[PDB]
């Protein structure tokens, strides 16, 4: 239910914008900005390198679909890396904190 | 008439991410503190960074929170030996009737050391 | 109430003539842009020069265009590595009712790079 | 059964203390210290930023409960981030190594 | 509406005592010159010290004279080669209706050289 | 299906060699090089520290076995850290790009 | 007879990983561009890095792509103030009959700015 | 009577994490090397870091491993040109009867170059 | 067997009088603290001053208090950026049976920040 | 087969005009000296400027004389203390059968001091 | 067609005698290694000295062994932190049919560390 | 119990030969002075060189006289303005019952100026 | 009647604060700030050192009692050094200036 | 009879000229130059700051009148600070030296 | 009864030795070290300059005679400057502290 | 016949290109490059400043029409400044050299 | 009648020598030294570049012939550039000053 979402961003402005929105919007509890990444990937059948930053988003399965949309809206890339890693087990109290601070809520007509 | 709002926040390192994230925190807490609803209430916002902070412009973080039409200005703060390192100071010129005694000034992180009164 | 007017202009070299001529251009274009008739409409004017500009004081150029009774102030701008070199920034504090959306901010020469929005 | 635990610490001293202890105390076989993290999160209904470091702890599900306690004892935070990510597959002899060095 | 008040004072050495004592002199003379009764008339006060003055913060001197609720901001002034050394410049943003021609600006010690007109 | 593989390398040459090779050989669609790791681990019943770099390899389960062999061939360590973390869910289009660039 | 192939690529930071990965990209694109099948077609390869790139030897990246028996040489490029920062330049001496007009020279990343003709 | 134990370890970079982790390795290897059971066997421990290591205090790492009651002291090592860079040297003053020939001194990482005899 | 005694004192300025007075204060408080009657109880005494203290030799202060037959040695302490400035550290090698837990280590002035445990 | 042509010219100051004009003179004199018809005879051209010449890239002057398709490369020359100041050196790799004894190498201005034989 | 010959030699100190005597050794060993009878087989020879070698020009040593008609060029080598100090590198452009696999490259003194493959 | 033996010697120049030869002189004179027959009587030996001595490690000379199993340590001595230049100080920690008054401390060459009492 | 009062203060701010107030409050005609004093004194039966600054306050015997109170109010120390030295004789005109500016 | 006269001068040139003249003209036996004074005082009913130097003149009551005149002649100020502090007691021999060198 | 004794010493070693001794030996309650004095005086009918340090000794008239002797014993000068200035008035509590710490 | 033609160019590359071409093409016998000009002019009814360089072209009347065309071809500006100043008198021999190296 | 004579000199020593001489010998009223010229010209049928300085000589037609000779005597070049440009109109007073100081 609680998961760590990885997002690769091109710059610190992108990192800070996406990072703040997600937390501020209650889509994630915490975001870690890991700087100085050197990314090697395939771009039009040629292996190319780029400088990026890694976002470690502390979220949940519930928030993920909206998070996905929101990140897409704020991300400059056409195909952004939004990949969720499951939290197997954890600090009971921390995961609670994550639950308190993650969740966009519903309407029951 | 204008009333100035003062703010100070400290960063642990000279990284753009750090500077940007900290200025966002300060800026918003300053507005939250004084219950400023619109950015239109701001005449302009001046910033000062310590000599040990050169990786980013704090004005760029104000734009992240959507202060595009707000006039911004940043300058180098006086390098007093032994002063609190890595400090982002803000002077927001706010268009208000509010008394001097009624403006709330925000000092965050180790910058609390700057105004304990 | 006060509204800040922002301006930025770049010079090709650090020569007093260059600095003086460029600040005159910016200052007048800023006033022209907002249709400011008298200098009396100005509360005060703040300037910031980049670290690579030390040959002249921009305030001295404002006086060349007759801004004697206008309070002027200049400071060193943050030396962000890889930022736009040789930039004279101006923050004119203008006494006006004008909305935030209705103030026109002037970005001249390579300083257009500074606000393309 | 073998997992990668993520721990966010406030300083390098906290990092090195916690990292060394876990490995020394056979609670983990390896710890990776990733420095210079800028963490944006919600603290008392307000979005705040802090400077931290990431620990990538190589442990087992069996070690996890004791690891959890030990990390709590050494960590200055009241609610520390101790979150385990499952290892789907990997270089087997290395996984053995991790299991051998987690007692 | 706001009117800026300009000041300038020179110190003989870069000592905290010198900086503190000189700014108080300057600060008070600016208020005395314009007959400002309360500090509440001040929107904010900006200071600029020359590169050869780093021993003290002028803002700390304004607090000695009791300007706690007054927003203060200091920055490094442009190091123009051959400019007047050891100069503390003040830009007080004063909330007043007073005409531009009616504000009195104070230039003390060798800082008289700065505005002989 | 899709996994994020973690590889700890001793140097930037090792990082760039391994990274380029996996992407070039269509064994990974993307590799992220995370520098400045400080690793504390057990080496011959003694806790030792070393300077490393982290590789974040975007691949699939089907690709993993060959990736494992290839990484082993290119890695200077006898028993390298090659550990796959499962992708729970993700950007549908991204995962498609990943699958496309892994052949 | 020999024909030189020119190449330029820019890096965002001075990190060995960055330098190595970028020189691999340039080197291969240069060979791909001219359809060079074997490394035996190369007499030697010379490299030049800008003053702001000191973390790695570009020659080490050519060896990563298996250019062991290819003679390599790197040197410091002229530090022209205001020139494009962090540029890795390559001069491959290629043993070919190919006319001057028929050699394809590769300018990647911000290094496109270097030859827009 | 006291017997001094010598140690040397090299770090790849000047980062606090690196310095702390390396001194912990050396400090324990040195103890484990002589079969030191309690820290009470240590009179005091002296450290020397090379000129190129300034990010952290090695004494702080000894405290991480619980050497609180152990007296620690660190000093700058002689900057001999051409000497092995980034070296943390330790002199532990051990209260023992052990002969000179029976003490084992630890030289780790590139610091093996320091005592090949 | 030897037991090391640690001490630390901070000075407000780099003046010989300051350094002298401060070291006398600490040395005596170190001896009184462990009830050392005879200076003959001291094997030797090592001192370390921070990089910002160069005006005097702390060993000269030990001699003022009559430690002539006591072997003394001073060295430059590691300049960790941002560490406590102007610190005089002492490591007295004391010939005693006293347990590790029973030695009293003295931190005076802002040097209390160094050992709050 | 290739034959290298050597050239050297000195400038009186480090000005782009000076550097550009001088490299044009040298380059053409080198070609005139060996009677080089087209630039297609040039495999590539390497340049070295002394440490006291940083205002311009000699390769840009080559382009002023249409050497667009010729591969060019410039690097920093060895700062031998007391060597001839402000020297632009050229190594043109010329595709020719010409004997070693029959190639004419050009040393202009004070650079005549470099090869008086 | 041209084949580049690589050479590297290390000197113990930055003395002209050292530099000259070592480059002579390398140059001749390179020629001996490939059985080059005449200097006429050389298109040109490029040299690179490390930042810690500035006392002499290696081209002057080539002239001592009579390579007057041979075009020579020297440049500053990339100062990669922790790279092999005091290294004279040579890239001789040799006019030959010889395969890439059949050229013998010379790495002398501590420069053997540079190519152990 | 341990007794420290103090030694000081001055060198005329900063040459390895000078440093090595002088430390050998001091070391032996110190042992001769106290009639120390075996090096096994030494707990450890600490050295301090002045800022103007960087060409060699004094510990390397202890080894020339065969103190391999003796723990050695050197550090930078306090650069007190106008203090005795080029001084090698030695603190030998000697395992002895000898009273403080019965240890003989050696001050050689201009280092006699250091202890005239 | 006219005296030179010595006041030892802990800092530059303390000096400028006290010195200006006294002069402004017509308590003294002139105050001289002597910096960089290294004070040695007895503290809880232990000889201690502190960096202090000296104030040389030109005042009258008549002002002294109010001066004493004022200095106490502004001084951070519980027992501040306020000691008056008598002016035996002096420049007639100067002493007149002193008396004039002490009201 | 023996006094310590205090004189505040605007500069080191003034300080040294006045000091030397007094000692040379046997008007004092010794003069101490205390530099780095920051003096806050009342000048024309307004508090102003200067940054002066202090002279500590060892003289006699008998020399004082001539000293007063001489200091006035050499001092740039219209009303210079010339204030004598009485020596209650002292080193018998020193006071003898002071009296001897004041003729 | 309470006085301020002025002592000029040649150095800081002397300034500190003398200062500490007086306070430690209950001959004074407090000593202020004023450094950087440039001292012009008459030495054998010739005006000479020296670099000194001023000591401001807070003591009593009762202490003075032993103080005088003790200072003489510790002072390198044959005829040291030991001159007592009377405290006309003062902070009641401070003077009490001074008297208490002078026994 | 001989005139001094003034040409204002935007850069040193433009300066050296135009200057070399005229001299090489025998349209000028000599060109002088005057650097560091700061030009104030009217551009679209607004006074603007630009950084420029001045060319002092030594040519003849006979040479001017072709020179005009050539400069236009090489100049990046739409309306370049090409203005001829008449040589009233001069060094007979120099003017001969100028005429000789023109055509 | 009044002209502006242009002289190109190879060095600052030549500039100052020629400039001073003309003005001193009343051959010119004023000389302006314009430094840092990069001159491209034809020398023996080859286009060459050289560093020079420009002299702007304020003289009369009447002085010109003597000026021509004098400049030749002081100039190191065989054929020096001495070219007179006519003054169409000017500041009446200035031209008077020029004529006054040329005779």
Image (cartoon, coloured by chain):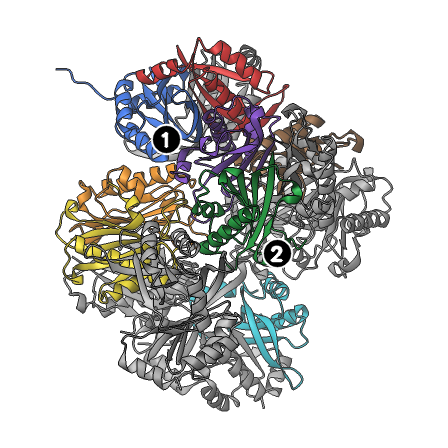
Chain colours: A blue, B orange, C yellow, F red, G purple, H brown, J green, O cyan
- Image coordinates of residue A52 in percent, x first then y, are 40, 30
Relative height, residue F19 to residue C112 (above, below) = above
- Image coordinates of residue J111 in percent, x first then y, are 59, 55
Using the rendered image of the protein, determine whether residue B107 is visible from the camera's viewpoint.
no
Residue O6 left/right relative to F5 = right
Circle 1: is it few (<14), some (14-19), or many (20+) Cα within 10 Å? some
Residue A42 left/right relative to C69 = right
Residue occupying image coordinates x 57% and y 39%: J93
Q: Chain of mark 1?
A: A
Spatial separation of the CA atoms under disc 1 and disc 2: 53 Å
Work out which quarter of the rendered image holds the N terminus of chain H and state it: top right
Residue B17, quarter of picture = top left
Work out whether residue H38 or residue H80 is closer to the camera in this orientation and state it. Answer: H80
SS for tag 1?
loop
Circle 2: is it few (<14), some (14-19), or many (20+) Cα within 10 Å? some
**Mark nearer the viewer, 1 or 2:** 2
Residues marked 1 and 2 touching at CB (< 8 Å): no
Work out which quarter of the rendered image holds the C terminus of chain H and state it: top right
Using the rendered image of the protein, determine whether residue B69 is visible from the camera's viewpoint.
yes
Q: How many marks?
A: 2
SS for tag 2?
helix
Q: Chain of mark 2?
A: J
Which residue is identified by label 2? J112
Disc number placed over residue A10 in the picture, else none = 1
Residue A54, quarter of picture = top left
Work out whether residue J102 or residue F13 is closer to the camera in this orientation and state it. Answer: J102
- Image coordinates of residue A53 in percent, x first then y, are 40, 30
Residue occupying image coordinates x 40% and y 16%: F101
Residue occupying image coordinates x 34% and y 42%: B108
């Amino acid at each position: 239910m609680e998961e760590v979402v990885l997002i690769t961003v091109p710059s610190a402005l992108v990192a800070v914008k996406i990072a703040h929105a997600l937390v501020e919007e209650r889509l994630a509890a915490c975001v870690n900005i890991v700087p100085g990444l050197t990314s090697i990937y395939r771009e039009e059948g040629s292996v190319v390198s780029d400088h990026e930053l890694l976002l470690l988003v502390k979220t949940t399965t519930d928030a993920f679909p909206k998070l996905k949309e929101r990140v897409k809206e704020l991300h400059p890339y056409e195909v952004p890396e939004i990949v969720a890693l499951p939290i197997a087990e954890g600090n009971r109290e921390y995961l609670d904190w994550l639950r308190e601070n993650t969740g966009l809520e519903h309407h029951h007509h | 008439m204008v009333r100035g709002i003062r703010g100070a926040i400290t960063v642990e390192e000279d990284t753009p991410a750090a500077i940007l994230a900290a200025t966002i925190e300060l800026l918003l807490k300053m507005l939250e503190a004084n219950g400023i609803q619109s950015y239109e209430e701001l005449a302009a916002v001046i910033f000062t960074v310590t000599e040990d902070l050169t990786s980013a412009f704090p004005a760029e973080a104000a734009r992240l929170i959507g202060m595009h039409r707000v006039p911004l200005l940043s300058a180098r703060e006086v390098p007093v030996p032994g002063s609190l390192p890595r400090v982002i100071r803000v002077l927001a010129l706010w268009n208000t009737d509010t008394p001097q005694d009624r403006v709330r000034h925000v000092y965050l992180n180790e910058a609390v050391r700057l105004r304990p009164d």
